[PDB]
Image (cartoon, rainbow, N blue to C red):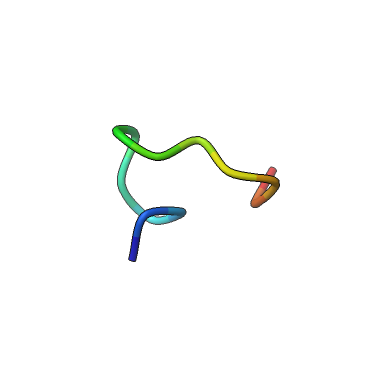
Length: 13
């Protein structure tokens, strides 16, 4: 998941 990985700092704050 992108949210789980730092490479993808989505809205998943």
